[PDB]
Image: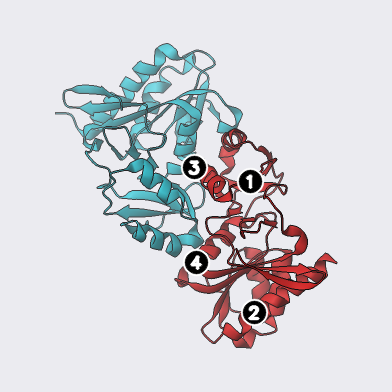
Chain colours: A red, B cyan
Amino acid sequence: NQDQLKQAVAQAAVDHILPHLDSKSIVGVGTGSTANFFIDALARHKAEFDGAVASSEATAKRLKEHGIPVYELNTVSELEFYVDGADESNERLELIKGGGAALTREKIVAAVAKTFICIADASKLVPILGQFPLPVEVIPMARSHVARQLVKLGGDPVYREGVLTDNGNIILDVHNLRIDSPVELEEKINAIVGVVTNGLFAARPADLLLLGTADGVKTLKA
Amino acid sequence: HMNQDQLKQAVAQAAVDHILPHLDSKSIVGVGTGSTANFFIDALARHKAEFDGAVASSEATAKRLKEHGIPVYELNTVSELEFYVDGADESNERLELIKGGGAALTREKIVAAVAKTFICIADASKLVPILGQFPLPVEVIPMARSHVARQLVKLGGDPVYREGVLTDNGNIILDVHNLRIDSPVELEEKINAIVGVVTNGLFAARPADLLLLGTADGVKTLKA
């Protein structure tokens, strides 16, 4: 099932990074269901590295519960690895992220990491991004303005009722985009004043995609 | 001789003079934040019986408006906003601005985006040949501080975290020194490409539409 595919890619990421780790290693860590399997698998090797940088309060809490040191991103200039899930990837390793509402700090940690490993079950690999609605984090008082600007880009935005991110912002999930050019669209959405971050990880895509399939975990590159 | 406050009052009143013939009972005015905007609130409030109310660009401005008896509406309740009136830290001759000295750049930039006509009101000293002597404010997610600073250094700036300041949105500001901003629209876009940036203080892709400049010899009315 899906959970066992998530468990598999989480373990695959641990196995991949393990030989690279040493007492100075600080691992960047995602948020959400797949990342949580990764946290628990990584913790079984906590003696092999220094600590971690979290992409959410929830992730920070889970890491601490395992006795893994959690450091603020502000204390590093680079991380060797950032490991996280996604809602969609295309074959160029351009992603839609933000289902779990943590897209902003995730995108920031990913920017500091040298190698972004995305871990996902097979169903998340799509020919063209956009069937999964694109999350956009928005300053709350900008809701109506940003929605209007997203309509101009050909989307149907929907406010995610009752949700505030770790940063105190709302999310508009944008339906009905056919995202043939994710790098271009990511830039267009960043041109909208009131947008904090958008869920396209395209200008800085994943570097490695570990995909959990019925035939095992496959390693994909752009 | 007019002091800086008096020059600010002159442009505040000039802005009221400009917009008044265009206001009716359903007019909602977008309002900036800071010293010059506050003088504008003083002048505008004398006419509160002639228009509906205002949209604020900060919690401080919302308080000032209410203290003057002007109704305050959330931006989310409007789509039609004819005027936004605010100060700036610098303008060039193309009405491209540096804003954010008063730390309100994000909500200011959002309200300005909704308004049809952005009137910038400023004293003479704020008109400069090239933007950048006034350090450029950039609003940043707090956990992104070191990352964004590194990316701003790559653009030729010297970013300095503004001690003890959190914006209305819970973010920090990096004030970026030493830029000579020859192409404000291009730099604005480049800074927006840095993940961790919330907004930057260049109002260039959406510049001011009208600049009222207070000088010793009267108010100047400038356009790009």
Q: Can residue B142 be spotted in the picture?
A: yes
Give the numbered dot on residue A112: 4
> CA–CA distance between discs 4 and 1?
26 Å
Disc 3 marks which residue? A191
Q: Amino acid at mark 4?
A: Val
Element class at badge 1: loop
The spot of residue B37 in percent (x, y) is 37, 32
- Same chain for mark 4 and mark 2? The answer is yes
Foreground: disc 3 or disc 2: 2
The residue positioned farthest toward the left in the image shown: B1
Q: Identify the image quadrant of residue A154.
A: top right
Chain containing mark 2: A
Q: Identify the residue shown where x is 42% and y is 22%.
A: B45
- Same chain for mark 4 and mark 1? The answer is yes
Reply above or below: A151 against A93: above
Of label 4 and label 1, which has the lower sequence position? 4
Of label 3 and label 1, which has the lower sequence position? 1
Q: Are marks 3 and 2 in contact (CB under 8 Å)?
A: no
Disc 2 marks which residue? A16
Q: Amino acid at mark 1?
A: Ile
Disc 1 marks which residue? A179
